[PDB]
Image (cartoon, rainbow, N blue to C red; front, side, top):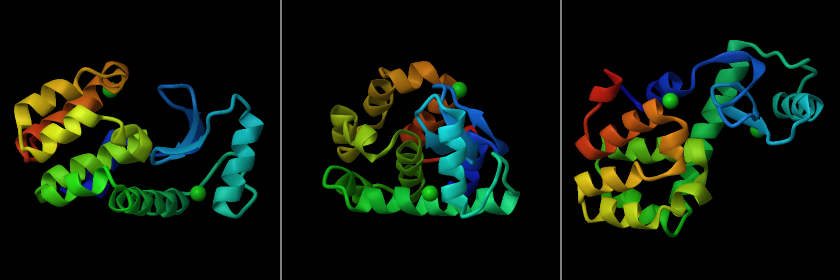
Length: 162
Ligand SMILES: [Cl-]
Ligand SMILES: [Cl-]
């Protein structure tokens, strides 16, 4: 089990523009296209992202190419972030994956905002961090995915995905 497999379980694979839990135009492996109601604004973003005229449809390889870019961007955003970097440096490899999961899903800015949890992660206060992370919109909107991520953070094991 690794971050790629973990995220592919959490996000799925879809070759046709679709909407996410929030209502946004998404595609492939959790790749947010636009927060704009326009399906045409989505298709335009998508063709731009892919470099071709897609008509809102891509191949598995294209979704994988996007996924690879997004994981890389997630990792790099963590490492370039003053609030995020220290937490990550302090964690073991499983837990690191958890933070990358969150960052991919909610953005760097989003996660960086979880002030108290971040402080608990660093202090290696696992239970408390798990409890505090559950007190969020994230958790209330996508409870099963969130529980999985929270268990990973709390335990340092990959059970939830097994
Ligand atoms: Cl892109
Ligand atoms: Cl869910």
